[PDB]
Image: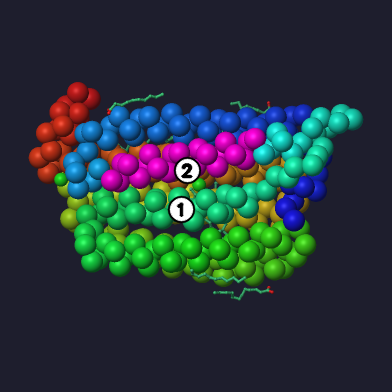
């Protein structure tokens, strides 16, 4: 049902996708160790925001690892090209994984925005429901990326509505609670918003690849877009969230945070 299954791949195409996914694994698990070691310099009220980045690194790292092994399982070099064998490859499992990873990305944002108690629970709940609506409708949509492009587009439109509303909740909370943020991170959090807008928008672009480039090079392009988007939305984003957590910790008087920033 996926466009990947339609084509044979050159040695170059096949190996490049393998390298993309493998590099993705390495970057996330390398970043994982970074978040782990810096977590001790984060104040208790923010420390979970850094822990969530560890959770995202392993979650994303495992899905990229799984995709890479699926890639090599599904294809074999036969008569001059990589051809589909008995096992299958699908991006569908990425969608399933977003059901967990996207709430984690949103939660760590709410934490450094200094949301607490009732407002935190209610905001998280609405955000997660919006994200799940986006993901599920998008998942349904890509089931038709070969059979029914018109249906892919309509489900994509519904998904985009959830996307836009989710982003509106995010923007509203960010620009409202920006003033509560310490150590100059009121400025930094604005860049985080724009980073999210940019990085997350790459995913619906990848979703539409079967509509504007239905060929083997389109398959490569989609994996390339996922790679850019994954690294930007999880790793670079996580680094900014953790930076914001540490800076606010230091400004709140947390001594390990103050000492850590002093060494650099
Ligand atoms: C780490 C993974 C992340 C941040 C994934 C984000 C995914 C999206 C923003 C997906 C958006 C979609 C649309 C807005 C329309 C087409 C269907 C989706 C699910 C690909
Ligand atoms: C930076 C270099 C990126 C690697 C290019 C891989 C594409 C190829 O070799 O076919
Ligand atoms: C934050 C951005 C992260 C960027 C990650 C991507 C790094 C590698 C990117 C691709 C370089 C282009 C490689 C040339 C493609 C050759 C075409 C092919 O062989 O199929
Ligand atoms: C392989 C990676 C091993 C990582 C172990 C690092 C332990 C961190 C110690 C700590 O700060 O609590
Ligand atoms: C095939 C029917 C798809 C139904 C989509 C349900 C939308 C999910 C909404 C928020 C949870
Ligand atoms: C909750 C929203 C559920 C779906 C809204 C209906 C619009 C998209 C569904 C398309 C159905 C189809 O193409 O057959
Ligand atoms: C051409 C790859 C980069 C595309 C970035 C633009 C999409 C996000 C815009 C906000
Ligand atoms: C080319 C540019 C690529 C961008 C690479 C991003 C690298 C890591 C981001 C680190 C986040 C630190 C937050 C900003 C620090 C500060 O505000 O002074
Ligand atoms: Cl604290
Ligand atoms: Cl993920």
Q: Quadrant of ligand 9?
A: top left
SS assignment at label 2: helix
SS assignment at label 1: helix
Residue appearing at x 57%, y 49% in the figure: 94
Alpha-carbon span between mark 2 and mark 1:
8 Å
Name of the residue lying farthest toward the front: 86
- Horizontal side of 161 relative to 213 (left or right) equals left
Residue 67 in the magenta stretch? The answer is: yes
Q: Is residue 179 above or below residue 13?
A: below
* Residue 211 x, y percent position in the rendering: 71, 57
Characterize the magenta stretch by its predominant secondary structure: helix
User: Does mark 2's beta carbon lie closer than 8 Å to ligand 10?
Assistant: yes
Residue appearing at x 20%, y 28% in the figure: 260
Residue 27 in the magenta stretch? The answer is: no
Residue situated in front as seen by the camera: 146 or 220: 146
Residue appearing at x 53%, y 33% in the figure: 25
**Mark 2 near mark 1, Cβ–Cβ under 8 Å?**
yes
Label 2: few (<14), some (14–19) or many (≥20) C-alpha neighbours in 10 Å: some
Disc on the earlier residue, 2 or 1: 2
- Horizontal side of 70 relative to 7 (left or right) equals left
User: Does mark 1's beta carbon lie closer than 8 Å to ligand 10?
Assistant: yes
State whether residue 259 appears in this view: yes
Q: Quadrant of residue 173?
A: bottom left
Find residue 100 and name its label: 1
Residue at image mark 2: 59
């Amino acid at each position: 049902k996926n466009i990947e299954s339609l084509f044979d791949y050159s040695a170059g195409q096949f190996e490049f996708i393998d390298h993309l996914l493998t590099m993705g694994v390495g970057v996330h698990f390398a970043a994982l160790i970074f978040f782990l070691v810096v977590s001790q310099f984060v104040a208790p009220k923010y420390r979970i925001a850094t822990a969530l980045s560890c959770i995202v690194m392993v979650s994303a790292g495992l899905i990229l690892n799984s995709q890479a092994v699926m890639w090599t399982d599904a294809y074999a070099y036969v008569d001059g090209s990589y051809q589909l064998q008995d096992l299958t490859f699908s991006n569908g499992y990425r969608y399933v994984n977003w059901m967990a990873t996207i709430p984690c990305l949103l939660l760590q944002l709410l934490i450094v925005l200094n949301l607490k108690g009732k407002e935190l629970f209610s905001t998280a709940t609405w955000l997660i429901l919006a994200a799940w609506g986006m993901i599920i409708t998008g998942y349904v949509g890509q089931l038709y990326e070969v059979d029914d492009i018109a249906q892919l587009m309509i489900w994509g439109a519904v998904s985009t509505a959830f996307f836009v509303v989710m982003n509106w909740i995010v923007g509203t909370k960010i620009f409202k609670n920006r003033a509560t943020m310490l150590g100059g991170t009121d400025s930094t959090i604005t860049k985080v918003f724009w980073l999210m807008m940019f990085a997350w928008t790459l995913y619906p672009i990848a979703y539409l690849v079967p509509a504007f480039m239905n060929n083997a090079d389109g398959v490569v392009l989609r994996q390339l877009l996922f790679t850019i988007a994954d690294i930007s939305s999880k790793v670079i984003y996580g680094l900014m969230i953790t930076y914001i957590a540490i800076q606010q910790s230091a400004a709140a008087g947390y001594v390990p945070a103050q000492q850590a920033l002093g060494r650099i």
